[PDB]
Length: 153
Length: 153
Image 1 (cartoon, each protein chain N blue to C red):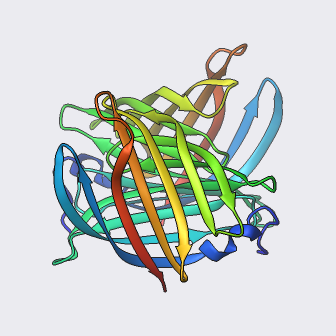
Image 2 (image 1 turned 120 degrees about the horizontal axis):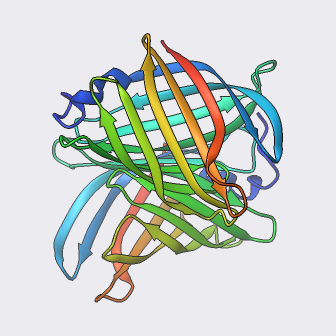
């Protein structure tokens, strides 16, 4: 199907991406992971998102998440994500065509009592997809949790 | 990877399913759809769920959803789902090994102001996957919305 007009400004996402990331948080010693993301569509004003992570040495699976990105022509966007850990997120924010960036903050995090907010920010940098995930908890204000850079396949 | 012990009681789900369903609700004239569901895993105590629907005549895409099922050996289960419409669900309930059934009700429905609760109930019937989705809204109590039967491929 053709790309819906509302998806076309984010057409640079469409495809599969692979790279690696790092996590760290005040309670949690640093760790690294491999990551794959696929963005796809079926002609609707929605981009399907699917993601998985693995251990770098072995390729052993770690976690997975999936959901849907819903951009609108005013530059607004909402994103819904379900995670293999048992959390859900409703993310809302904006995308910027000139910067090839997407900036999201949670309206809601479901099923995760200690986690309060999650933000997710993407940027295309020299054709690579970079992001930062930030997380707050009851006692820790919003701050970096995950960062990754992925090459387009 | 081997099937995790917590997933093994639900191993009958694993695979791809295709069939058809029907929707109806007091505000909403009946409609029909084709449906495909895949359940998969990667050796963790989680089953990945992915679903799509289409128009019966043409195969034109309708909607999609995806998420994760997390069964536990006490018979409890939680399910998280993100939908292409922009909703999320946290579903909790039980599974019954003798009946090959799964009964879920939402703890949370996110990003959908009029929708209050969703329940989802699955049953294996003569090797086919059947479900019923029920929905409440502010003014309509919980009642059937969707029902479908799918054959295992």
